[PDB]
Image 1 (tube, each protein chain N blue to C red):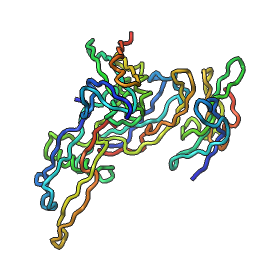
Image 2: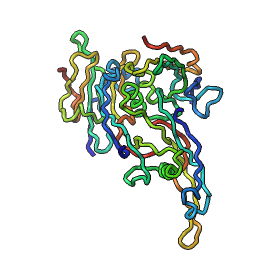
Image 3: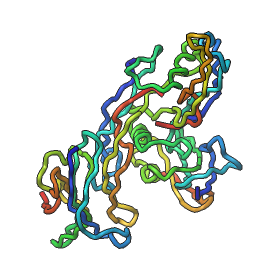
Image 4: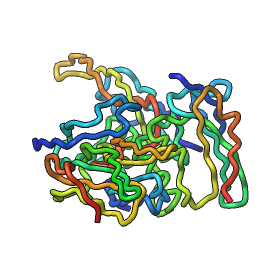
Length: 84
Length: 103
Length: 104
Length: 93
């Protein structure tokens, strides 16, 4: 395992100090639910299928922006903003 | 509320297996439950299919989300009575949930 | 309503909004699994010992959920796509198509 | 088990540490068809070959002995077919 990431909302059960270990990417996401209510989350993403998840679908019904990064604890610096 | 492992102790006398199984009295089986949201994090060990299905669900709610199930199970041995009152030891695979994920 | 089995599902990349980075194919038949895992679990149903134990437990403790219908056999498809640098890449994505379903 | 061989080509063989051209023996799962494919760019009438190789079972390639692109004006052309070395030559349409 090479990468450590911050996690919030998406932490595994073996999470320590709100960080997780992965061999893929770190991510951060901002999402707007049924109501104009916004929430931020972050965590670890496996390499397999990460191209799909980091790209996401621009046709998603709810507004959200996920971003990915690949160096140790990098997601603390991702500040995704909702799409217009 | 997201997909994770939950507790589940299976008492053999509660499911009528104690007349067949001499030992153990029961065991910790656990179970998996919870939402598979977008995105599917590393620990959910999801297949590409589950990832694609989650994204389609996000575009069209008519397509269900992936489901939280055991992605890793382990074995347990159990002691049974042979038709001779001979206590026989047998291994049973896939009895215990070791990990949960979205499939 | 119905028993655990494969259902049709065609994933169209234009509808997902990926037709700009995926050169081929335009889409594919992914299928999905859906349906109940009723007690007693039907033999033809692909089921693990755990799903069997859980189903039995659920029959006498409704607080424990039933097993779930999910992909148990999947196949791969080839995709050709453009990376961040507009470079063409070939990848055989594993587990993209549901071939069979089961209660887990 | 049905066997399939395709023409192999990789314009980025260097940065990918692979052969630039040659032959590729395909491997498929049971009862799965086996195909070949070609991809290229056509900028200013000059054809730029990008990649050629094996391609997994895909209905878009079923029973086509010729490799013909099925997209009007893409930025990257693609064709697939079902037959040994059927990606040896390709055309647009």
